[PDB]
Image (cartoon, rainbow, N blue to C red):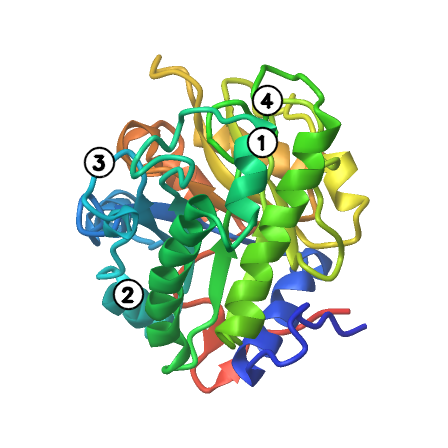
Amino acid sequence: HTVSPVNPNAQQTTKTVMNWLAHLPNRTENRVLSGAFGGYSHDTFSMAEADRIRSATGQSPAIYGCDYARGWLETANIEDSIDVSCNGDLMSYWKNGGIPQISLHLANPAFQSGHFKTPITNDQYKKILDSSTVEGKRLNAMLSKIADGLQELENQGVPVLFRPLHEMNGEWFWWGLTSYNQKDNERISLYKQLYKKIYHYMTDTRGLDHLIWVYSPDANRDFKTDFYPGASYVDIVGLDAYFQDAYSINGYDQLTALNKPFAFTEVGPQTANGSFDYSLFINAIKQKYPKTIYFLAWNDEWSAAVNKGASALYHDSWTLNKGEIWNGDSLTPIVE
């Protein structure tokens, strides 16, 4: 069975990587890509996180993340919150045997700038969806700058795990729910519209053919599947999971049931307690979440490098690290 990107015009390299990723759970080893968040572009992004993991374990994460959007900033123009200077490092990461991932802590276009965690009403959200309003124009200004950055990677044929509008079932980001675990049918509909608006802007308006689209609800809130925009807009489903108990993460059954590859799209300790153990997380994957194709641990205090079990995580027979995607000029096996 071949798994093809949802974008019908995806570049060959992106098609190959998507099919390869989807088949990882058929392997007996090297079946879960490691990953780490590298930081926010021109703010905290650097190679330090990758280098610390390598110093701690001898291995580097297969996936390296950057976030273009510093959505807390109050800026003259809303799009000033976007910075794409991490691109060079992302392209180099691909060249050197890993895969880049981009997320977006978008500023809130209901406001002049910033306000990324300020909740908005459905009436405000409707304005954001309408390209003719000041709110819609602010959204499109951000999307345009993001797309300019993404184009740089496309020009070198670099596939990107693109994970927009994450944790939408949470109540913290402007694009999500407004109250804790409170179903709002209109908000769910509007979210799907917003995700599709970004999909169409990137794919059709901007012709971006190197993107693999990731849908990532939070594990610690309800409604993991209600926000799913549909099979034609999503390549990979996953959970952002911050926890103490690796074995009690909710949502894996619901998301794998959508018949898309599944990942732990963010992971880390819920609290800095000295109790968190990444060796237990990989064990939980083997026992509880075997269809997992990758994890992306956050940086700073959430980092694999500074938490217990880093070596066991990175050396587990299941873990696939930087340099293990390609075997020189050949691709490592696609198992059916």
Q: Which residue is mark 3?
A: 74
Q: Which residue is mark 4?
A: 220
Which residue corresponds to the image point at 26% horizontal and 33% vertical from the top-left? 300
Q: Which residue is mark 2?
A: 87
Which residue corresponds to the image point at 59% horizontal and 48% vertical from the top-left? 194
On screen, residue 133 versus residue 263, left or right, reads: left
* Quadrant of the snapshot with the C terminus: bottom right
Give the CA separation, mark 2 to mark 3.
23 Å
Q: Viewer-nearest of labels 1 and 3?
A: 1
Q: Earlier in the sequence, mark 1 or mark 3?
A: 3
Give the CA separation, mark 2 to mark 4.
31 Å
Q: Earlier in the sequence, mark 3 or mark 4?
A: 3
Q: Which mark is residue 123?
A: 1
Q: Earlier in the sequence, mark 1 or mark 4?
A: 1
Q: Earlier in the sequence, mark 2 or mark 1?
A: 2
Crowdedness of circle 3 by 10 Å Cα count: few (<14), some, many (20+)?
some
Query: In this view, which residue lies farthest toward the bottom?
Result: 329
Against 143, residue 222 (above or below) is above
Tell me, yes or no, if residue 30 can be seen here: no
Q: Secondary structure at mark 4?
A: loop
Q: Secondary structure at mark 3?
A: loop
